[PDB]
Image (spheres, coloured by chain):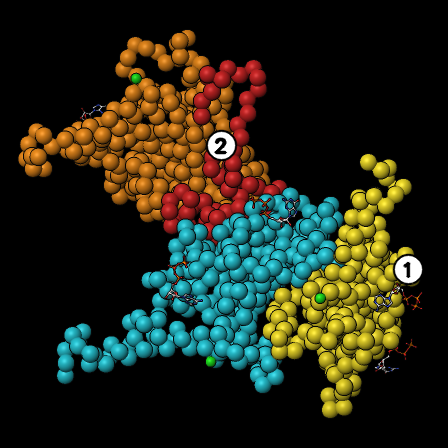
Chain colours: A yellow, B cyan, C red, D orange
Amino acid sequence: ADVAGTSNRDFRGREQRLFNSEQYNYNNSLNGEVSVWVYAYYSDGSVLVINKNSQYKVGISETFKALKEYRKGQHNDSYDEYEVNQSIYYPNGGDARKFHSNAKPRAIQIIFSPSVNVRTIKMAKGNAVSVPDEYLQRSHPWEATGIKYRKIKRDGEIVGYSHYFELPHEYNSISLAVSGVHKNPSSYNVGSAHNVMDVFQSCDLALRFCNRYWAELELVNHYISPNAYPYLDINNHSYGVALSNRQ
Amino acid sequence: ADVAGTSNRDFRGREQRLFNSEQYNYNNSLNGEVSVWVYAYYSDGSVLVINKNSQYKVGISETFKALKEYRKGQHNDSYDEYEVNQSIYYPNGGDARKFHSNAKPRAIQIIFSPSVNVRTIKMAKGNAVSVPDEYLQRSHPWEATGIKYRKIKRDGEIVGYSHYFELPHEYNSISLAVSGVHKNPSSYNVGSAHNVMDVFQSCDLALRFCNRYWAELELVNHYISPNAYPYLDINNHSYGVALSNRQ
Amino acid sequence: ETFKALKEYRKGQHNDSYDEYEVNQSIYYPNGGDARKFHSNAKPRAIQIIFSPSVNVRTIKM
Amino acid sequence: ADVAGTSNRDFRGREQRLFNSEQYNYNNSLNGEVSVWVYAYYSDGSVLVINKNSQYKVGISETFKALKEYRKGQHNDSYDEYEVNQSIYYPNGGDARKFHSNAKPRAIQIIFSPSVNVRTIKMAKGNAVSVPDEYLQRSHPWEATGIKYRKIKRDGEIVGYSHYFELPHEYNSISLAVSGVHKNPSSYNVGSAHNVMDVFQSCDLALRFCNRYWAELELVNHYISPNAYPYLDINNHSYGVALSNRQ
Ligand SMILES: Nc1nc2c(ncn2[C@@H]2O[C@H](COP(=O)(O)OP(=O)(O)OP(=O)(O)O)[C@@H](O)[C@H]2O)c(=O)[nH]1
Ligand SMILES: Nc1nc2c(ncn2[C@@H]2O[C@H](COP(=O)(O)OP(=O)(O)OP(=O)(O)O)[C@@H](O)[C@H]2O)c(=O)[nH]1
Ligand SMILES: Nc1nc2c(ncn2[C@@H]2O[C@H](COP(=O)(O)OP(=O)(O)OP(=O)(O)O)[C@@H](O)[C@H]2O)c(=O)[nH]1
Ligand SMILES: Nc1ncnc2c1ncn2[C@@H]1O[C@H](COP(=O)(O)OP(=O)(O)OP(=O)(O)O)[C@@H](O)[C@H]1O
Ligand SMILES: Nc1ncnc2c1ncn2[C@@H]1O[C@H](COP(=O)(O)OP(=O)(O)OP(=O)(O)O)[C@@H](O)[C@H]1O
Ligand SMILES: Nc1ncnc2c1ncn2[C@@H]1O[C@H](COP(=O)(O)OP(=O)(O)OP(=O)(O)O)[C@@H](O)[C@H]1O
Ligand SMILES: Nc1ccn([C@@H]2O[C@H](COP(=O)(O)OP(=O)(O)OP(=O)(O)O)[C@@H](O)[C@H]2O)c(=O)n1
Ligand SMILES: Nc1ccn([C@@H]2O[C@H](COP(=O)(O)OP(=O)(O)OP(=O)(O)O)[C@@H](O)[C@H]2O)c(=O)n1
Ligand SMILES: Nc1ccn([C@@H]2O[C@H](COP(=O)(O)OP(=O)(O)OP(=O)(O)O)[C@@H](O)[C@H]2O)c(=O)n1
Ligand SMILES: Nc1ccn([C@@H]2O[C@H](COP(=O)(O)OP(=O)(O)OP(=O)(O)O)[C@@H](O)[C@H]2O)c(=O)n1
Ligand SMILES: [Cl-]
Ligand SMILES: [Cl-]
Ligand SMILES: [Cl-]
Ligand SMILES: [Mg+2]
Ligand SMILES: [Mg+2]
Ligand SMILES: [Mg+2]
Ligand SMILES: [Mg+2]
């Protein structure tokens, strides 16, 4: 046989490159996943991730309360935190024993898979009582925020998209939903009558994951990296695996 | 009057047969329910059922964590079980005090009502971090598993469909979503423009039920049987009520 | 060892100690107890008996 | 065939009688069990049974403390009861908050199986510090109490032997060991050199049982009766199953 790495008959090499390219491109086919992640960062360094993975479209929607830090199996000031919520829902509405709940997110990062079409991204960033823009009557139910998404790149390939906003002020008390649609460069509408029931089934088949990791280090090591997910850390370092035409 | 059970003028008998046939056939009309049940069996003999009942289509989606046994009002090693989850999400990722959580399901049974079309059944059986097939990039978001569904029969009538798989190995750690579409032998597409908003409303109107029963006996006696639901027990015994052309 | 002594006991952790009294009553006589579980996960799933190579196997009794 | 219950060819009847006679006589063979039960009766009506079943010989030995009522999974005044014990071991030796512990047995019944030889029965009924007769130096380590054992009879057959003594006074604070030897009408000594190691093995093979039942009713119903054990209740009623030459 020919010697490795020296000729056009390195079939092991050709197959390796195809294996990777096939994965990149499968993800972008209409048969592929589109995935969204919401990372809620807490002052103690821990991070709640909520991930949803589905065909065609995908999204996450959380209440103010659901985005607050919850330490499984530990004390959470659960009564005081009911009282905190009452004062967040209406000023001077509760009887809490703290000015600022350290369970409130300090920041949110939203990441989409590279199979999303960024122009389809929509965000409903509501107030603490789940209203998008001050009052329902004048609320558009979303903002199209794709222009703000940065490309997470590795080796020159787009491995994901990130929108990050800090919530560092006392008044940054939010509810949050986000949504993106899978790339579809074709003129086959996946929600036209021929395939619409499959999109309805995709709503039932969407897989959800949620967990609080103790530190960004741990998220990078045990959540992002093992699963070949895209990420951007606090030091603006990009994580992910470039696959297209790559060995 | 004619004597009962002796002539074609037993109207009480005719009405009884129609009453039953009407129910079988109503369920199969597009006005009818389609229902799915996920049974998660635990080593202590208890069983979590999640049921969803809706028009047109129906499905259930649960995280790894949500399928774990939770004993309401009793101790659940809640801190250790956070640690268990960390080691299930990534090997050697947690600091638990047990090798195997007895809260992990030992088996799953998926049952559909007889109004499902088995060829529409789709399952997303993911890993513990809610990925269908090892990595998102190469994951088809579902498998069409209808061929594996057994018919639950009573008196010769199909009263439901069952797919059962055990999770007896240490590595059987799953997330799970399943979906089926209601029978529609017509060429009226329920999700075409004339009726699509009704299917969107059906997503909001789907009724959910979940509860942990202490034993299969108790599930059969107090969940399955009172509600005329189909079931298949560990001894391969079929439960349900035959209705078509029956008194 | 008794039935009870072979059951799992987690030193320094919770063991459903009251419910497990009730489990034992139903194991000693069917329908004899008032437990909140069908199967106690504290029951052994298997037993291995090992002897040293200095045993005479023909003397083994169980 | 001959008609049942009318002739000497009722083989079903002959076999039934042999089946029963074989059990009575097997128990009395040297291959058979000898069994002892100690019942400790508490003021709340509950009863601790300790049973031991072995070949050749059998016995039970318990400390003062081990004979005290212990309610599994409930509160037992465990600290105060340490203090009670200190005052029982030496007068005015402890700092308890009660004059009389209701955990002290009110009575003891000792029962042997009908395979015991009553003349071999020996009892060490010690004081609270496990001394048989006031001081070790002058203590015989047992008393041969067989003469006091009453026969528990059913249908004229000896189904067991009972010695019962109440402990109704404040000073009845005891330690207790009892022992009996299996019938051996032969001149083959089971502890002579030919079989002595088998008796040593019988010491390891003796099976023990202990449990606190809530009432004498419950002991009769769920302990004594299901297992064909002999008993004598507070109303002097005999329980057991006659087997010799019986259908
Ligand atoms: N400035 C301000 N914003 C409020 C207040 N209450 C709610 N908000 C919301 O805060 C959102 C903007 O959040 P931020 O960007 O963290 O506040 P900012 O004033 O821009 O401060 P910087 O981002 O740090 O420059 C707006 O969309 C408002 O709807 C308030 O009392 N003052
Ligand atoms: N065999 C194996 N399967 C794994 C492992 N990790 C995850 N799995 C998943 O296990 C799934 C199959 O589960 P099982 O059917 O219970 O395993 P099995 O090897 O077929 O064992 P049996 O079903 O009892 O014959 C596969 O789809 C794998 O994706 C692993 O380390 N070994
Ligand atoms: N009488 C008496 N017996 C004691 C005392 N201390 C220990 N004992 C033991 O109590 C045992 C006898 O118990 P009982 O039969 O309940 O006492 P009793 O005086 O015979 O009273 P009755 O049996 O009700 O007639 C004796 O063997 C003594 O060793 C004590 O202070 N007085
Ligand atoms: N919508 C898209 N989805 C996936 N890949 C894309 C998309 N658009 C361009 N690419 C490819 O991704 C790689 C990077 O292109 P891109 O335009 O992001 O890089 P750039 O010009 O260096 O940076 P930027 O546009 O962010 O300033 C190229 O191979 C490009 O063909
Ligand atoms: N998709 C269906 N939905 C409901 N009923 C059906 C369907 N297909 C067939 N039936 C009816 O159900 C009854 C049983 O038919 P079926 O083919 O399941 O039984 P079978 O041939 O004895 O068993 P099997 O096909 O499982 O080997 C018949 O009345 C049949 O007409
Ligand atoms: N040591 C023994 N073991 C077993 N059975 C015996 C023993 N001695 C006698 N028996 C038998 O038990 C039955 C009852 O005999 P037993 O002498 O106990 O009754 P009794 O004379 O009516 O009453 P008691 O001797 O208690 O005043 C008879 O069949 C007798 O042969
Ligand atoms: N504004 C507040 C806050 C707390 N408490 C009291 O604080 C007690 C315990 O604190 P809690 O808020 O419940 O937190 P933890 O018990 O410490 O932690 P967790 O409840 O999450 O286990 C509660 O009984 C509650 O009555 C109160 O009276 N008023
Ligand atoms: N790997 C572990 C597991 C448990 N614990 C400690 O175990 C204590 C109590 O056990 P827990 O896991 O919380 O279970 P339970 O309290 O018995 O039951 P539950 O919390 O569900 O009421 C907790 O305070 C926790 O700190 C720990 O330190 N490390
Ligand atoms: N069949 C049962 C089982 C439990 N309980 C109640 O459950 C409470 C606490 O559960 P327990 O069985 O005692 O287990 P744990 O306290 O969680 O753990 P452990 O007692 O071993 O520390 C007890 O007070 C008991 O009264 C009950 O009433 N009936
Ligand atoms: N003579 C005594 C008796 C009891 N106590 C105190 O009583 C408290 C609780 O009573 P306890 O004797 O321990 O019984 P319970 O806790 O009610 O039941 P248990 O310990 O068996 O669970 C203990 O902390 C112990 O310090 C004491 O100081 N002095
Ligand atoms: Cl495609
Ligand atoms: Cl219809
Ligand atoms: Cl013999
Ligand atoms: Mg706890
Ligand atoms: Mg609290
Ligand atoms: Mg307890
Ligand atoms: Mg105590």
Please report the residue visible at 42 percent of the width from the left and 17 percent of the height from the top: D199
Question: Which residue position holds label 1?
Answer: A156
Location of residue D128 in the rendering, given as x and y in whole percent from the top left corner: 49, 32
Marks 1 and 2 on same chain? no
Q: Residues within 10 Å of mark 2 (few under 14, many from 20)?
A: few
Q: Nearer the viewer, residue C11 or D177?
A: C11
Q: Residues within 10 Å of mark 1 (few under 14, many from 20)?
A: few
Quarter placement of the C terminus of chain D? top left
Mark 2, secondary structure of its residue: loop
Q: Amino acid at mark 2?
A: Glu
Question: Which residue position holds label 2?
Answer: C1
Mark 1, secondary structure of its residue: loop
Location of residue C35 in the rendering, given as x and y in whole percent from the top left corner: 46, 52
Q: Nearer the viewer, residue B58 or B140?
A: B140
Q: Quadrant of residue D227?
A: top left
Q: Is residue A42 above or below residue D171?
A: below
**Chain of the residue under label 1:** A
Location of residue B17 in the rendering, given as x and y in whole percent from the top left corner: 30, 75
Q: Nearer the viewer, residue D232 or A151?
A: A151
Q: Separation of disc 1 and disc 2 at Cα? A: 67 Å
Circles 1 and 2: CB atoms closer than 8 Å: no
On the question of residue D77 being in view, the answer is no
Numbered mark located on residue D238 in the image: none
Mark 1 near ligand 4 (CB under 8 Å)? yes
Please report the residue visible at 58 percent of the width from the left and 61 percent of the height from the top: B144
Q: Is residue A169 above or below residue D117?
A: below
* Ligand 4 - quadrant of the structure image: bottom right
